Image (cartoon, grey):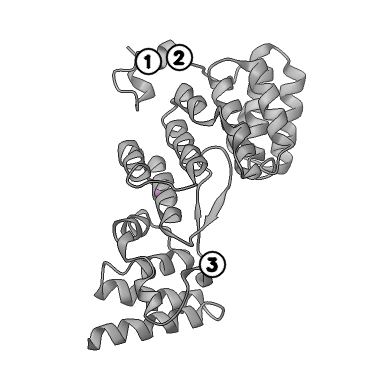
């Protein structure tokens, strides 16, 4: 009624304000969600303004049946907001544009995986058909399983990646396959897959995991000068405390597991529970 008109006009203003001031747009999108917690489009607006609080992504997901309703009442396509969400998990820095509820699903699953809410992540992934986007769900499962160190389940999800349309995501999948191999002490396989994935369109987005796991594979095989060369490259290009630490200490090694060990977990989601 009166409130509908008010929220419409706040949304329209928020979108117009985006090139001028994300801070002011945020105030307006937040004013909408304060009055209507179900206003999916305004939760997405908040994400666009740099609000990636886990609750904001949860709310966008929870209100997903309202996607398009508020923006639609002022004739704005949600694609015009140019909101993006994180979907790379541990493998790389990969974002995806929020142009449909699929994006929200993927973002929510990645965020839940990061928080350790794996069943909730999986349940969101399986809540609806994916309608020509099977590879995207497989990718997100690889993210969720990887977060829980379920390396054999990662491989199950990405082993088919040669047949994916999206060559970027097929490349990312090769990184996941290589990381999973390394964590299972399949170091030669890890080196082949990570080297190939490095040539793909995902090589840059996944540069950190690619170099780290190559270095760890080389070190565990005994090839210390290769490991050091990769870690020196990392400290130059993507410096990090654990890279500095690994470069200074040759006993710094990847702790690996096996299919049998993963299967013996009292709780498959908990790498600490190996019986
Ligand atoms: Sm999170």
User: Is 101 on the left or on the right of 254, as rendered?
Assistant: left
- Mark 1 lies on residue: 263
Tell me the quadrant of the picture where the N terminus can be found: bottom left
Query: Dot 3 lies on which element?
Result: loop
What is the quadrant of residue 238 in the picture? top right
Label 3, residues with CA under 10 Å away: few <14, some 14-19, many ≥20: few
Residue 111: x and y, percent? 41, 47
Residue projecting furthest to the front: 131
- Mark 3 lies on residue: 82
Ligand 1 under 8 Å from disc 1 Cβ: no
Residue 275: x and y, percent? 32, 11
Contact (CB < 8 A) between labels 2 and 1? Answer: yes
Label 2, residues with CA under 10 Å away: few <14, some 14-19, many ≥20: few
Mark closest to the chain's N terminus, 2 or 3: 3
Q: Which mark is residue 259?
A: 2
Closest to the observer: 122 or 132? 132
Label 1, residues with CA under 10 Å away: few <14, some 14-19, many ≥20: some
Query: Dot 2 lies on which element?
Result: helix
Whether 129 is drawn above or below 66: the answer is: above
Residue at x 24% of width, y 84% of height? 3
Closest to the observer: 158 or 218? 158
Whether 232 is drawn above or below 50: the answer is: above
Whether 239 is drawn above or below 213: the answer is: below
């Amino acid at each position: 009624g009166h409130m509908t008109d008010r929220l419409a006009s706040l949304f329209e203003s928020a979108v117009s304000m985006l090139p001028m001031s994300e801070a002011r747009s945020l105030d307006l999108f937040t004013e909408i969600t304060n009055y209507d917690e179900s206003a999916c489009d305004a939760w997405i607006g908040r994400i666009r303004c740099g609000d990636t609080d886990r609750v904001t992504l949860f709310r966008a997901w929870y209100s997903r049946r309202n996607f398009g309703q508020l923006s639609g009442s002022v004739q704005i396509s949600m694609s015009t907001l140019n909101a993006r969400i994180a979907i790379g998990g541990l493998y790389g820095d990969i974002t995806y544009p929020v142009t449909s509820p699929l994006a929200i699903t993927m973002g929510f699953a990645a965020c839940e995986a990061a928080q350790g809410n794996y069943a909730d992540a999986m349940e969101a992934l399986e809540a609806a058909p994916v309608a020509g986007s099977e590879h995207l769900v497989a990718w997100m499962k690889a993210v969720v399983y990887g977060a829980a160190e379920r390396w054999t389940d990662v491989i199950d999800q990405v082993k088919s990646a040669g047949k994916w349309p999206d060559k970027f995501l097929a490349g990312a999948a090769g990184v996941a396959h290589g990381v999973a191999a390394a964590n299972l002490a399949l170091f030669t396989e890890a080196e082949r897959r990570l080297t190939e994935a490095n040539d793909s369109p995902a090589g840059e987005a996944c540069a950190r995991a690619i170099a780290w796991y190559l270095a760890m594979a080389r070190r565990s095989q005994g090839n210390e000068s290769a490991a050091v060369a990769l870690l020196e490259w990392l400290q130059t290009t993507h410096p990090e405390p654990k890279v500095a630490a690994a470069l200074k200490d040759p006993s710094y090694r990847l702790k690996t597991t096996t299919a049998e060990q993963i299967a013996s977990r009292a709780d498959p989601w908990d790498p600490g529970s190996v019986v």
